[PDB]
Length: 158
Ligand code: NA
Ligand code: NA
Image 1 (cartoon, rainbow, N blue to C red):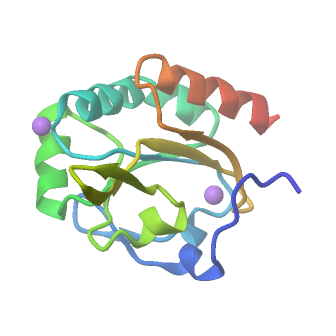
Image 2: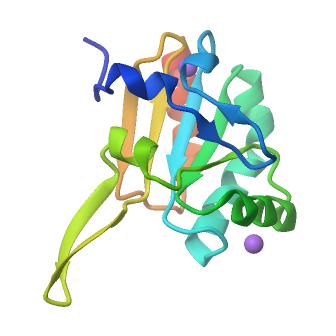
């Protein structure tokens, strides 16, 4: 009833490779809020702006007990390099096989170049402490976005 998206049960048990070398799963985040933001490519202008915006708000997300995860299909090494250069203090998921992306339906198609072209669409989601996807943002406008996500989280957490 409060969910805006339904994920396959197996999604919650997928091993998610993180920057820094560990793995997590969505089920492992039970009991707290989780922000999951998908972005198309490490170390590009919009993706860097977005990451830095979430990073600046980390104390506010902490106040609410929430954790953040950024997601792209870049490698663990790429993610480590991106985190170190930018000073990110939250983890990035290396979704190399796009399993997490597909679960959240963020791989979108565009008819371009006389081809059917698939790519990550910038998207963010709020996962409740009980594992429900309760809010979504798709075709994300980076400017103002992290602020909007924080505000929505606060409104939901009540
Ligand atoms: Na970088
Ligand atoms: Na959660």
